[PDB]
Length: 347
Ligand SMILES: CC(C)Nc1ncc2cc(Oc3ccc(F)cc3F)c(=O)n(C)c2n1
Image: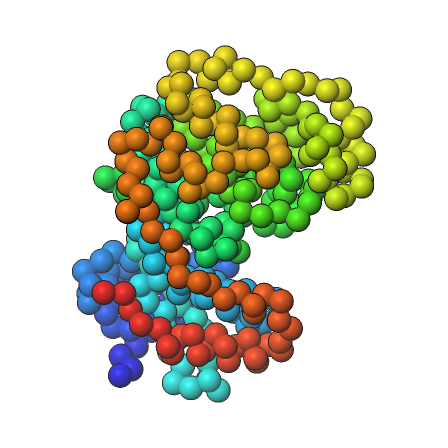
């Protein structure tokens, strides 16, 4: 049955939430809405509550609202953000206007942990293992994160990690000396080709390197500067990769660059575990077809003490046929409404 709702103004906005949620307090921006910390009296969990801002103001917005709800409803994995609750104060589709999403409140993101400093190899092992464990799961559902970065990786006191914001940035915020671009695979940064799951492994490589050194791997001042930093490390592309750059314009620019060989990673990451160096070399391959997969990386010797093939689950099938579907605002809205109503809380 329908719980009782109460009203409260927080982020210049009226929040109407079930009584179970108490002590609501703003904690910053999330994807497509503002996030509040709260205490869920029913579960005893500290939770993050996101109220979506104008979820159905356009077809793009309506579809994006539906997309986020579908994604969050599907994810049931220890190392991936999951949906604890979703609600609306609306009593019918007719009065349906607002969507609230509830998940675990996380302690800190990976940026707060790196803090300009080197992490110990054992800490890097555990953190990267969990990212890859979550990624294996996400990828098995044919979902791509597309924007993996330290700020999207949340970690508790026991170093247990969850991946946030998968499967969902304007040109302006990708411009210049910005972390929004530092972790992006070159093929996606410069739109070389139709990208796939392998873009996420690139991001993991960049993250792992940063955990090991305490420094951004490719802190480019712009797209071109970043590409130069990338190619200096991994080498300029060969004829084989060049053929796969379907963009004639991008392909033509690449060939204008003086050729460079791949650097020696042992000389770049001085003092690092040779097994860490080996893994980095397999993740940071320019040709995406040849990058190590999440499933393969889990079996790499670097994770010997954590790897357990019987405790690295895959996802149920995820139907994303809706992505190629053209619908009106109210149609996306009705689909979203059905998803809200049908929600079953996790045990
Ligand atoms: C201190 C910080 C690192 N902990 C933390 N914890 C949770 C979230 C959730 C976010 O997003 C949500 C996703 C799904 C939901 F159901 C609800 C949400 F609020 C979000 O964007 N951030 C930044 C978060 N941060």
